[PDB]
Image 1: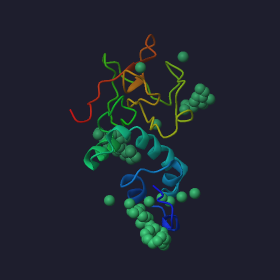
Image 2: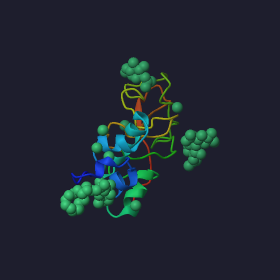
Image 3: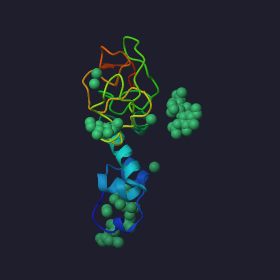
Image 4: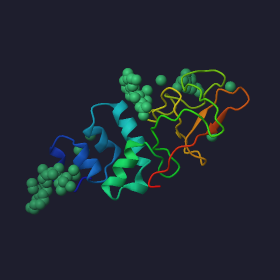
Length: 146
Ligand SMILES: CCCCCCCCCCCCCCC(O)OC[C@@H](O)COP(=O)(O)OC[C@H](N)C(=O)O
Ligand SMILES: *[C@@H]1O[C@H](CO)[C@@H](O[C@@H]2O[C@H](CO)[C@@H](O)[C@H](O)[C@H]2NC(C)=O)[C@H](O)[C@H]1NC(C)=O
Ligand SMILES: *[C@@H]1O[C@H](CO)[C@@H](O)[C@H](O)[C@H]1NC(C)=O
Ligand SMILES: [Ca+2]
Ligand SMILES: [Ca+2]
Ligand SMILES: [Ca+2]
Ligand SMILES: [Ca+2]
Ligand SMILES: [Ca+2]
Ligand SMILES: [Ca+2]
Ligand SMILES: [Ca+2]
Ligand SMILES: [Cl-]
Ligand SMILES: [Cl-]
Ligand SMILES: [Cl-]
């Protein structure tokens, strides 16, 4: 947050400016050292608004081992779908040509074949499946706070 006066003379600090106070994308950018880091942080940050209080809740959401809300914040290592289908590598173009990837969604952390919810799918974190007949399916990930 920018209370207006001279705080902006200080070098950006993520803890002070974004975690101890709400911040704008530009503030986050100033506090971080790259666009990559900014895209990643901003995606995790916005996906955790429903959990900014208390800090323990916010930190858990940002860590992303559990899904908050619809799970756009999820960054865990589950790579199998609900029905048990092994997830397809996000970077692979087979058996399904991904409409969603690193380019269309930077900061979504679409690594390997881990489940993610880059488009805010209502059924939670998902992944393109290795089954030729099923393009994508949601995964079973633990919900934050339960
Ligand atoms: C330099 C003073 C300018 C303000 C003139 C108003 C009258 C005097 C009252 C003083 C209170 C307001 C101080 C505001 C100001 O300029 O902030 C100085 C900054 O350098 C401090 O920055 P920083 O610690 O990052 O921001 C404040 C915020 N509570 C935080 O934790 O981020
Ligand atoms: C979750 O998955 C990540 C990503 O594969 C694992 O971290 C990687 O671990 C390898 C060693 O096995 C390192 O070479 C990589 O640098 C790590 N990837 C990065 C840069 O994040 C991590 O160990 C896994 N943890 C769990 C929960 O199993
Ligand atoms: C992302 O998708 C676009 C078109 O959908 C494609 O041009 C690009 O090569 C893809 N890259 C990834 C993230 O695999
Ligand atoms: Ca501030
Ligand atoms: Ca600021
Ligand atoms: Ca700043
Ligand atoms: Ca602090
Ligand atoms: Ca403050
Ligand atoms: Ca600024
Ligand atoms: Ca700036
Ligand atoms: Cl396809
Ligand atoms: Cl990868
Ligand atoms: Cl899905």
